[PDB]
Image (cartoon, coloured by chain):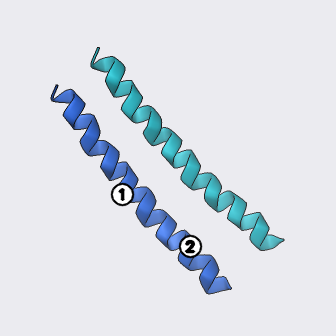
Chain colours: A blue, B cyan
Amino acid sequence: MQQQQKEAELLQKEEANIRDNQTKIIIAQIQSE
Amino acid sequence: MQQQQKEAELLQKEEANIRDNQTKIIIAQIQSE
């Protein structure tokens, strides 16, 4: 359960980080308007 | 209970982080005005 504990928070950080990268490109396209 | 303790603060950080990303796009659209 401690591994099912930690594997959740490990994938939490990578998908949080893509979501910051997804917004950093879409802020650029509205600045390209 | 300690896992119900920690799973609350783990989802707390991811939804806090989307809410920062939600505001970083909406500040850009009013700057696109």
Q: Quadrant of residue B6?
A: bottom right
User: Which residue, as the protein is rendered here, is positioned at the far left?
Assistant: A32
Give the Cα distance between marks 2 and 1.
Answer: 16 Å
Q: Along the horizontal axis of the image, is A25 left or right of A9? A: left
- Name the residue located 40 percent from the left edge and 34 percent from the top edge: B24
Residue A27: x and y in percent read: 28, 36
Placement of A4 over or under B28, stated as above or below: below
As helix, strand or loop, the secondary structure at mark 2 comes to: helix
Q: Residues within 10 Å of mark 1 (few under 14, many from 20)?
A: few
Task: Pinpoint the chain carrying mark 1.
Answer: A
Q: Along the horizontal axis of the image, is A28 left or right of B12? A: left
Q: Along the horizontal axis of the image, is B14 left or right of B1? A: left
Q: Residues within 10 Å of mark 2 (few under 14, many from 20)?
A: few
Residue on which the image places disc 2: A8
The residue type indicated by label 2 comes to: Ala
Residue A26: x and y in percent read: 27, 40
Residue on which the image places disc 1: A18
Which of pointers 2 and 1 lies earlier in the amino acid sequence?
Answer: 2
Viewer-proximal residue among B9 and A32: A32
As helix, strand or loop, the secondary structure at mark 1 comes to: helix
- Name the residue located 45 percent from the left edge and 33 percent from the top edge: B23
- Name the residue located 40 percent from the left edge and 28 percent from the top edge: B26
